[PDB]
Amino acid sequence: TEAQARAIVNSALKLYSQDKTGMVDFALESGGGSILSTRCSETYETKTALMSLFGIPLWYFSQSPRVVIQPDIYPGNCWAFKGSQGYLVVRLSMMIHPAAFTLEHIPKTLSPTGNISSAPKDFAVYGLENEYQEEGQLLGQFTYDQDGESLQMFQALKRPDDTAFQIVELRIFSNWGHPEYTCLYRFRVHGEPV
Amino acid sequence: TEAQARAIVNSALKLYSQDKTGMVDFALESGGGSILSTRCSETYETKTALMSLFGIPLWYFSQSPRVVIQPDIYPGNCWAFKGSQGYLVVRLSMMIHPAAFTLEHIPKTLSPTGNISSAPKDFAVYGLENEYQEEGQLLGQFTYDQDGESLQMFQALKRPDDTAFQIVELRIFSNWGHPEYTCLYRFRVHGEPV
Amino acid sequence: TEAQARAIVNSALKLYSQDKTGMVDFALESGGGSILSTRCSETYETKTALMSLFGIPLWYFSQSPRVVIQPDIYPGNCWAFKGSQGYLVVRLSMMIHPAAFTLEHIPKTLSPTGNISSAPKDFAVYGLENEYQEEGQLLGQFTYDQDGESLQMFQALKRPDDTAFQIVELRIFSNWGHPEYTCLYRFRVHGEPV
Amino acid sequence: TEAQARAIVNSALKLYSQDKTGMVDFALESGGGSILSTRCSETYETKTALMSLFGIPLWYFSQSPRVVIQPDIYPGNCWAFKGSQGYLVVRLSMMIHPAAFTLEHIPKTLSPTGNISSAPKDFAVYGLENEYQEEGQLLGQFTYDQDGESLQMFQALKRPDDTAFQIVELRIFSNWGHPEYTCLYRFRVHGEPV
Amino acid sequence: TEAQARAIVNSALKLYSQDKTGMVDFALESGGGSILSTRCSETYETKTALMSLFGIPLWYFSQSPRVVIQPDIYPGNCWAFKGSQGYLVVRLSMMIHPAAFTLEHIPKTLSPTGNISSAPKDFAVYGLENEYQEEGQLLGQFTYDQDGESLQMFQALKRPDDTAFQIVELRIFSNWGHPEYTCLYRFRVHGEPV
Amino acid sequence: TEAQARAIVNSALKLYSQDKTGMVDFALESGGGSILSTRCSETYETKTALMSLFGIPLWYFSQSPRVVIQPDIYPGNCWAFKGSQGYLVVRLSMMIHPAAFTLEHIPKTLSPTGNISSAPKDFAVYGLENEYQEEGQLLGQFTYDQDGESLQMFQALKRPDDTAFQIVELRIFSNWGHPEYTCLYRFRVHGEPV
Amino acid sequence: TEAQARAIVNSALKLYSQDKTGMVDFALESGGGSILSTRCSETYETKTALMSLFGIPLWYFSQSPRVVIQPDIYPGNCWAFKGSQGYLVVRLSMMIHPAAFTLEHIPKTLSPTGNISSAPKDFAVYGLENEYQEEGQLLGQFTYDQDGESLQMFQALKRPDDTAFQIVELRIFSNWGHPEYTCLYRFRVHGEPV
Amino acid sequence: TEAQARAIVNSALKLYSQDKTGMVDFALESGGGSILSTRCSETYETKTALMSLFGIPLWYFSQSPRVVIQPDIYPGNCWAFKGSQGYLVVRLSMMIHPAAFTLEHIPKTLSPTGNISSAPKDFAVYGLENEYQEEGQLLGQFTYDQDGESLQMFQALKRPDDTAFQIVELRIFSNWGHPEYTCLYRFRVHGEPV
Amino acid sequence: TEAQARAIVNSALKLYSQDKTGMVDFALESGGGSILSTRCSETYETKTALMSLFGIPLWYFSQSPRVVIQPDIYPGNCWAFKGSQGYLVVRLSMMIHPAAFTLEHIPKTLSPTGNISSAPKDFAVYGLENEYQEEGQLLGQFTYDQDGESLQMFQALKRPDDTAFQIVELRIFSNWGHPEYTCLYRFRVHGEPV
Amino acid sequence: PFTRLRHNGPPPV
Amino acid sequence: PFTRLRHNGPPPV
Amino acid sequence: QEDSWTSLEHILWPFTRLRHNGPPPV
Amino acid sequence: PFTRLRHNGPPPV
Amino acid sequence: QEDSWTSLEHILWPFTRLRHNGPPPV
Amino acid sequence: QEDSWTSLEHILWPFTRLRHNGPPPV
Ligand SMILES: [Cl-]
Ligand SMILES: [Cl-]
Ligand SMILES: [Cl-]
Ligand SMILES: [K+]
Ligand SMILES: [K+]
Ligand SMILES: [K+]
Ligand SMILES: [K+]
Ligand SMILES: [K+]
Ligand SMILES: [K+]
Ligand SMILES: [K+]
Ligand SMILES: [K+]
Ligand SMILES: [K+]
């Protein structure tokens, strides 16, 4: 069973090295995904991360919604939107039949605050035919489980047809209790190109 | 034992993915840690990092002590301070009882010279009650072993009183022989919030 | 043998954490390698520009060749050159006897387009005594296998003599079919310093 | 006849040194002439002259109509307007009674293409009383002869009165056959100041 | 005694014209002193910024610490640091044995707010052998008296030895009650050059 | 009487050092006063103070109305407005009951022209409730006496109530004869904060 | 004699406040004097004045001869010219009969070295009829006395004819021993306008 | 013979005006020639050309190999390459059968030193079938004669096959004695388009 | 004698191509000469500026003095100084014994205004041992003849001694009548290097 | 957008 | 005019 | 505008100091 | 406001 | 705007490389 | 706008030369 153990380990490390899932992320910014910033919720305003230069206060740092489609997920490498429900609109790198979505959040064991009450909880994903459409087509309703794994994957609804989209709206309907903001670490969109 | 093998493999990968330790790093900058840069020793002037804009090279610069609380540890992603003695002060993201510290350095197999003579060797960690306090509380005396693993963990002295700290000072007294500078790749602080 | 399984897993993870190879990359930018950009092929011209200034569109490119000696290899973090033939000139962090080379490309499973036709195919590596040398010394001829692993290593020609090099040229003679450009995600140089 | 030969040669070289004609060019930019750019035909759009910086594609070079009132006439130092008929509006350095016009084009013997099909052929020159006048006063109708000399001069129509102008419109009604564009190397305006 | 009165008046005016003290200020910027701004406390962050760039407010400060070694002391020409504890590090124009120090603050009669609660109160001066020295040599402990004169002078500790200093640190331990910041109008260093 | 002489001299020098008056100037720019530039008279246009760089004429220097609330009063450190009557609007650093005003002009003995015909003569001061109010409340009508002292102080009218202001308009109704402009060196506003 | 004492005191303060002399300075720049910078000797390259913007240090520079006709005379606010011989030409704000000249230097008690070896010593002043005149009219030969007062006044030679001047040349022949440069703090020209 | 004299004179001036040769230069940049700058030898770092903007000098720079295919040949308008050996590759404006090459250098009478020791001496020209071809076809071996005329023409070897070229490599093997660099003023390629 | 005619013509054209003179111009900028712009007269201030920035018009000039040592002499490619007297200081490319000077001006036949009243008339050339030397050595006094040729040459004074110069000053004492400015098209310095 | 802001709040004194 | 353009076309991958 | 700001932020990032005065969102 | 002005007046010649 | 661009082009010209990918207009 | 110009004027002031061609207002 030694060679079999090596095979299991190598297979797990291979999957791990492929963005943990082995699946194309069509939202990923470096691959061509982008945030439609005017269709995102308001970013949480905080004057507590002060950037200075030669001791001179220069500007207050806050993360933009772009970080949601970037792979780094160390604590704090997340977009914080104001309040406990909000939305994010993503233009995908290709026109696809969306098949599944991934949400990542830091595990509690790494959270400096002791909890992940700022994680998203109830959410839904919609396909938009253009950047001006309000609601779009429901692709699925889900819950990110604060007691589950850091990375959670969700299957899109099966429809009699396969309508393709290049714009998806993530609607976060609730968070896990944080009284000021909700933090999104990474959102991925998987599916089949046209 | 195949299911057990997969369990061992998955458990190791999960721990690996959790910042290798599975423990909150209260010094990590993105999580709320901060360098008190006026309370660091002198940066060695290396001018070995290139800055570019739109693909155009602009100028070379030296890494600041902020990289000590940032997770990237490829060769060169370290703060180089002048000589073989130095100090660094970090404000933590929470008031904690410190339990342990982690120092990382690149392994010898990744160092171009074959050695890590610039790695820190003897060091001590102090708890500070405020950022103007000159004499802090000794939390431990340690040696980073150049013949050990890249990531090394160090247990804090525990004292019967429950004094919590939100400021830590790292004092490096010696390095592994480099005559010009010492390179710190990453320093982490672990413990329990109050 | 549970301890043997844990040993297999820990060894594989240790090697994985050591830049996947456990070998110095003398080309790595943060470790002291650099692109000699005035000696490299011209970067692929994208269809649209990044900005406009005084009515003129400026910057028709995606990534500069520096990314070839940076470790992030998420899709799109690659240098694209025009067509299917090109060259990249790298100054190493030390004078070495080159022993092996590594080329990485994204796996097909992460490619948005479904293919990796833009991956390099036939290539050779030459050692140069200086960056203006017209004809270099052949260190080896190779093919990146699109059906192989993402990371591939190539053994330098066994040489009777020991001339060291601090400059290498990577020459790409063909790609895996993309009609517009070729994408290089990461190139590494391994060997023994003098 | 030796002194007479020297006199002939010196006289020819003198005339040559005086901008080839010995006549004031009131359109000449350095002397105060200028192009009214919003009243010129569309410039021919070509993405074939790529300017790059450190290998990075930067912008696509095309000549502006200003070069028509600049003396350099090496091949390519010409304004190319889209198609085979167009117009150029020039503000003169002084208010004048226009007496003659000069057009220069490269000789065929220097054309890399073997022909000068892009030279202007049928043209007319109009005096404009202000920059908003559509047609203006016809000052003459002419043909640039592709089989004649590089520099050709044309006499303005004699009018019972002498109306002065400081704006002239050059209308090119046809070229010598080039299917994409027409190239103007230099246009001069001669006459008497008021 | 009219001549004696004129003599008294001229002596007082002469001393007044000699920077009020008749003593070299080795900290004075125009004479060669300088602020080591990377070793000073952070400048107080004002509520609003000086400009905005690309929608981001920039520069939340009023004066830089350089004004502490400039002679103008009209209200507002002072360096404000956050809170009631801070420090300022000054390189002197020469290596000296420090003999005395001067602190100036505006008088209450010129303060718009009616008070000088932002004036420093308890402070100490240390000589440093270099700007990265953690613990300096105490040159003296003093209190600026809010009920005293605008300009106050303080005698350095009488010392058995003669170690000269070219760097001094001014440490402010308290102010006269302002809850947000402390304002330093001018600090001078007097003594004998080596 | 020697100690009494020293007391008189020291008292005079003290008052002199306190901005000559010992009174808060709520208009003073460094203390928070500011000019409302769109409510000031037109600045006198002169092309006679040429700034050049490397011999190249660069711009024509003229003083702005800000200099009126700056303490320097060497000849020429004044705002010149066009003609012989005009106005200046000042926002004060605090809301106050205005009690008195100060005007300074250079003494004739220092004027390069031999006279101070450009000094203000008849003027009035008004309190404005907001920056859009045309006339406001008359606070007093005065004359700056060209035969009096350089610094002249004027008492505000006594009113049955004390209305506070943070904006005052200085209306200059005449000058001392200069045919082109009127020069204001410094205007101060004194009073009691609310 | 108390009223007389106050009179003496007030008279001295009034004279002090009038640029210390009570006399027009026709060289003063803000009053209309100008340096003819092409007719000055070489500036010593000191690079000892710091330039900053928004609190950010940008670069060091040397003072220009313009500071000689500007009133600030704190240590370092001087033009340093190369060597111990130099010249400076100033155009006056009026055509005058020159009566006297003033040179100021810092007193020894304010000089960091204890001496003023860089002060000018022997000098002469010439009247020039136009700015291209090479041979001017000697207005006096003088010595600035390093053992005298900071401000020293020098009487012009008066000649029976009434030749007025609007251009003055200051020639410095020697300094008080500094081997590298000579420092001029302020030069003034007094007289009667025509 | 007077008419014949004028004919001779006019014929010589006409030929002179046609780029001195009356022949297409397929290397000329404005006509479509291009330097392949990654296939040129090292530029000598001279920093002897001044760049200015708005009359303000900004910095010094060295000429690039592009000046070799630009027509201005005043002293200094040349590419200086390091040492006495170098190479330059030019892509031609058309695919041609090369018939001849022209090299120009300044005449000795215009060189400040009296000699042209930096002029190229022995050189060879090769035809390249594509820009990656290492071994090209010898088109001729030549010597630029320092005792000859400024413009020298060189006849290509003609081979029976009709191989056309659009890329030419100029190899310089030696210069006329300058120990530091070699200066190329202009290189031209003549022939017949296919 | 047809061959003799061709010889006369070729000699005249050869001399013409050698910068019209066949003599080194040690002032020529591209050959190593330079304008010492801080020692030159101020450039003529045009009526309007080239741009505006933040509401202020900037750059009131036409050409910088560099154009005097550049060979293009189309109308307007000249340096204009104010009035009819001025000076230009040039550093030569080598230390030489000056033998002759050349001044060029446009011919009347190319002048838009009909005249060349702005051409220099009386002038002199001085050799300077350094650029701050007040009085130079007269190398000669001359008049540019407005009725002569465009290019005029002037013989340096015959000198008993051989002091070389690398800096020359051109002093213009008068022009040919223009009431506003004087225009210099090109100035050359010829001689023998040491 | 190099816009300049007006503080409207008095500086430290 | 320091305007920033949006590509709308995917980068090389 | 945001593209402009993020590229400027890239240039600024290494050279600035960052002080947290309270916990950032995590 | 980096605006570019048009002279409308001829340069020195 | 064109004046601004041409002055920037002047600054850029010597330092850029120029590749023709097809014949420019002549 | 005036704040921008005055800060630029601050940067420029020491490095420029100033010629009065007639008396400034005093
Ligand atoms: Cl931010
Ligand atoms: Cl262009
Ligand atoms: Cl101004
Ligand atoms: K992220
Ligand atoms: K790090
Ligand atoms: K990469
Ligand atoms: K042209
Ligand atoms: K101060
Ligand atoms: K003032
Ligand atoms: K001064
Ligand atoms: K050339
Ligand atoms: K010229």
Image: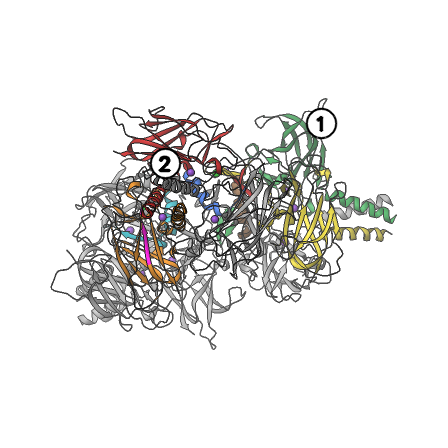
Chain colours: A red, C orange, E yellow, F green, J purple, L blue, N cyan, O brown
For image coordinates 34% across by 61% down, the residue present is C98
Q: Is mark 2 within 8 Å of ligand 4?
A: no
Numbered disc in front, either 1 or 2:
2
Q: Is F97 placed above or below C14 here? A: above
Front residue of F155/F90: it is F90
Q: Is F36 placed above or below C64 here? A: above
Image spot of residue A17 (x, y percent): 36, 44
Image spot of residue E104 (x, y percent): 71, 46
Question: Chain for mark 1?
Answer: F
**Left or right position of F5 against A107:** right
Location of mark 1 (residue): F157
Kindly identify the amino acid type of the residue bearing the numbered disc 1.
Leu
Q: Can you tell which quarter of the image residue E148 is in? A: top right
Q: Which mark is residue A34?
A: 2
What SS does tag 1 mark?
A: loop
Front residue of A188/F55: it is A188
Which image quarter holds the C terminus of chain C?
bottom left
Answer whether residue O23 is visible to the viewer in this image: no
Kindly report the secondary structure that dominates the magenta region of the rendered protein.
Answer: strand
Part of the protein shown in magenta = C100-105
